[PDB]
Amino acid sequence: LIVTQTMKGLDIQKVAGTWYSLAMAASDISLLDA
Amino acid sequence: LIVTQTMKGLDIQKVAGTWYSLAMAASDISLLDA
Amino acid sequence: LIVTQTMKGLDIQKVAGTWYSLAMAASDISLLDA
Amino acid sequence: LIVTQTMKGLDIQKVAGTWYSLAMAASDISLLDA
Amino acid sequence: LIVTQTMKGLDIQKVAGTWYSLAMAASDISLLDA
């Protein structure tokens, strides 16, 4: 697994609540949500 | 697995609630949601 | 598996609720939803 | 499997509820929905 | 399998409910829905 993530010139504004990331990379990602 | 994710010039505004990413990459992604 | 995902010039506005990504890539994606 | 996904100039506005992605790519995708 | 998906100049507005993607690509897609 080779991963490249690139972000340029984002404007992010008035984020409420909960914010985990902009980029995620793993061999496995597990989300358990309730 | 080779992954490339590129984002340019996004405006993201007034996000309420929950926000995990803009980009996700893995070998496995599992979401369990209730 | 080779994956390329490119996004340019998005405006995203007044997102309520839950938002996991704009881009997902894996070898396997599993979503279990209730 | 070679996948190319490109998005340009989207306006996304007043999204309620649940939003997983704009782009998905895998070798297998599984959705179990209730 | 070679897949190319391109989207330009979409306006998406007042999406309620649940929204998984605009583009999906796999070698196999399985949706089980109830």
Image: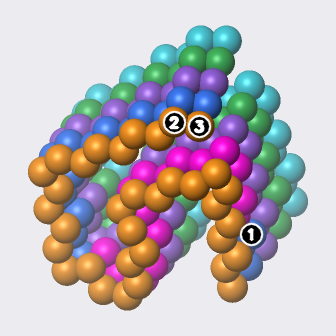
Chain colours: A orange, B blue, C purple, D green, E cyan
Residue C14, horizontal then vertical, whole percent: 29, 71
Picture quadrant of residue B5: top left
- Marks 3/1: CA distance? 23 Å
Do the residues bearing badges 3 and 2 touch, measured as CB atoms within 8 Å? yes
Magenta-drawn stretch contains E20: no
For disc 3, the marked residue is A1
- Marks 3/2: CA distance? 4 Å
Residue at 74% x, 25% y is E27
Instruction: Name the chain under label 3.
Output: A
**With respect to residue D9, does D12 lie above or below?**
below
Mark 1: which amino acid? Leu
In the drawing, does residue E10 fall left or right of residue A24? left
User: Disc 3 on helix, strand or loop?
Assistant: loop
Residue D25, horizontal then vertical, whole percent: 59, 36
Residue at 55% x, 24% y is C2
Picture quadrant of residue C26: top right
Q: Residues within 10 Å of mark 2 (few under 14, many from 20)?
A: few
Mark 2: which amino acid? Ile
For disc 2, the marked residue is A2
For disc 1, the marked residue is B32
